[PDB]
Image (cartoon, rainbow, N blue to C red; front, side):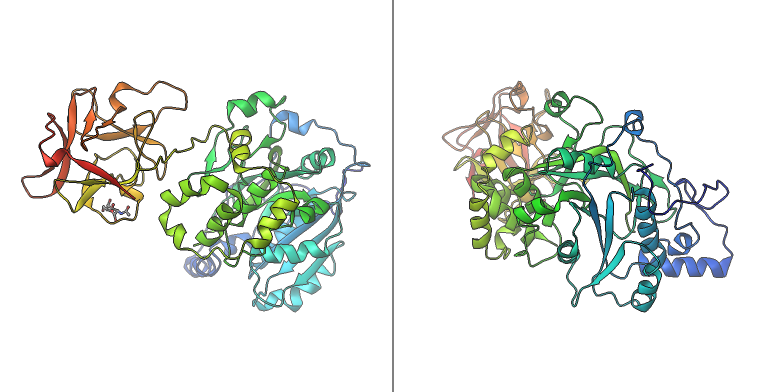
Length: 514
Ligand SMILES: CC(=O)N[C@@H]1[C@@H](O)[C@@H](O)[C@@H](CO)O[C@H]1O
């Protein structure tokens, strides 16, 4: 059986703590509780509990039925080097990862596990780790000489790897059965496919493995370039022939992926000119697809990750290198990004040219067509200042939940976008869209302004979200027949309201500023 792993799991034991990835809870006396809380304070993971769960536990496989009946040609699949970087990882989580890879991966395909110690200071990660891994076939340790960060530690590890395919996992993962074959099968069919497992959550407190059932969500972004999940679009459902086929993802949705080593090297690996840590996968995503490259999530490959209990320079760098004439939509909506030192991108431009990468316009149309791209027409986006109360700007401040909870109001003009950033559209909508596509609306028969999700591209614009910015500075709402007016509450607070129109009233006069 060429599916055989290098080491076999012991028989499953349903009496054993956390077997099958089920939740674990211990009965602890009061000293034991103190010990458990101490380790959570130090590790942000329930290490007390991890230490009592088998390093070799089974995870119950709940994948789509078609996944479990797939056949593979083990003689023709590519080999992989598994790369795991760590910094001060607890013993039991670090080792459960290693044993999990060793026990769930076909021996014929697992060339090596390369552990990268990114300048750990835990004493057990010096001598003791090397002694433990000296007993484990194909497991090697590489050590950095300085604190490199996840990406650069990974690069150092990849440099030592000689497998056909690099598979970057992390230091507190547990692999589902059959996780590897679907990645390697696909890359064996298309060497430019960067293929990601579905990343399931392992509970840091209970160690329950929560498997995503059926169709995963996939990766993209909003116009602040913050990562956002979205559902598989109709175009992608229709392109794919089976529901267990790989799914195209506009951006990477986690840190776990398999890529042909030669192909990763050809693309330039990660962007080394990044100085700050974090957010590096946006730049990588754009580069793979524009330089093409496919980025996929594979529904039959599941890896669990213990999620424990900024990087704007990197995000801006991705925009400067890749986004061409669309970067300004980002800067308009995340103004602090304009102030960030994204670094010298001369070498990156040359790499893009050498690789003959396609445009960001191409990316948007072909990779992320649904997504809405703002216009930000000159003179029609920014802050909207009141003529009547000259210190005040239109301002929408909703709770973090309930993005459409509040009413449009006034607040001191600060020039920083966000709650004061708007876009007047060619479809005559006033969009409040630094975060999501929200459209200013007057509900039927009312005289206040709220927000609601904008219509999808190409679909009817409701009558009650149409605004006419008159030549005279009036913001007229033709459906209500009223005009937007500044006023003060009886208590003195500036506010807005819909009033009968009067172009001689300076409280109904407004202007865009940027
Ligand atoms: C830049 C920005 O969004 N600032 C918002 C402001 O516009 C206003 O909504 C206020 C309400 O408390 O919060 C702010 O600091």
